[PDB]
Length: 453
Ligand SMILES: Cc1cc2nc3c(=O)[nH]c(=O)nc-3n(C[C@H](O)[C@H](O)[C@H](O)COP(=O)(O)OP(=O)(O)OC[C@H]3O[C@@H](n4cnc5c(N)ncnc54)[C@H](O)[C@@H]3O)c2cc1C
Image 1 (cartoon, rainbow, N blue to C red):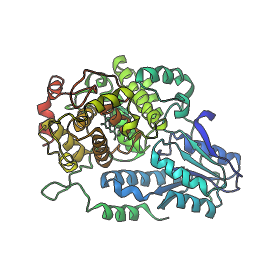
Image 2: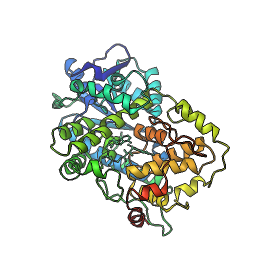
Image 3: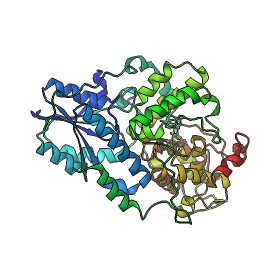
Image 4: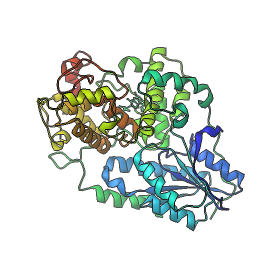
């Protein structure tokens, strides 16, 4: 157990009650450093461990596609945690008022949570700190190397964050120890009813077509830790060999499709890296996949951790802010509203077909994600309007939405974060441009459009 994975946010006097694991980002029982760190401290104090999840009031800011995927995975998690004699408590409302009330009611001895560099998680941490007198720690269970240990600084490029992450891999890339069950079973509603009431509250804002039928197809990704592992096994066995040569072709499903399980924390990235590193495949394809799940995934947490305004124009590089400001008054070719972007009613069939894959599957291809966001900057009134539209459409319809990957990805597409300056164009400036003809020379754009009518 590396002590560099755990951070102390506030000290205090330890109580003689159950160690509380405030689960948030990592919703799994296996390969969870935060849950394992809570069981170790609970064992050292001769007291069982408990897990608490808060169903926040911000669930209506998303959709049914993310509400059902999360709660259905939590239902499987409760059975898995109960088999280890670890009881789970699902509170509903403000985590600042619920976690404070749970710790005081149940006489908690130590509170533990998982690490998330997002602003909304820091908002909960600030409120819970104000009304708790017991120790409270946080553990990085999402990244292989802790976010505060990989770099003490915002890395402006992947060429600089790669040697720092790979030099610390022999230390943090290790096997997980078995989660020991509680010694004895210790001493606020069922998730089936919370799923029924929540869906009934999200029904009027459901994504529908003109025929009143639903648009989302929930048979593409089955939720749960069991299904998350089966997806990783299928990728290593069938798709990992052809990954390095077909990750940029949206007409072929050659990606790992592990992003919805990785966002909600249903599967550990360290577990995926461990199975891939010991797998024998194309070295060019293994290097490309490890570059995506290690470098670009953890540099997204690095961007959100060392940039408070990671979702704003101020976090852009100085060369991009100066380039975008010099082309602010440039006459845009087209100006579409948020409703026209949402329904995919633009003149570009490639962008519209990309938006249709986002609305129907909740997981648009990785290559088209760059074309989908860069066109928003080209057809918006201002770079700040492009950030708002793309963030809203990402977090609302992407199953992996509301994730540091999405915020670092959108910062690269429009703001050029972790990128370089390209040829100076109008409107877009020195931001890397992706043309429609450039996509046709890379893949069958006609098949990708015909698939998502
Ligand atoms: C405009 C835009 C929006 C995005 N929105 C999201 C989002 O809402 N949520 C989200 O998790 N990711 C987002 N991404 C990153 C990336 O596109 C997706 O992670 C990817 O499409 C997920 O599909 P996959 O896991 O099957 O691909 P794979 O090739 O199997 O990648 C595996 C994993 O590596 C990581 N990874 C790979 N590429 C990236 C990347 N560019 N950035 C960060 N991590 C990466 C991911 O964790 C990914 O799950 C976005 C990127 C862009 C440019």
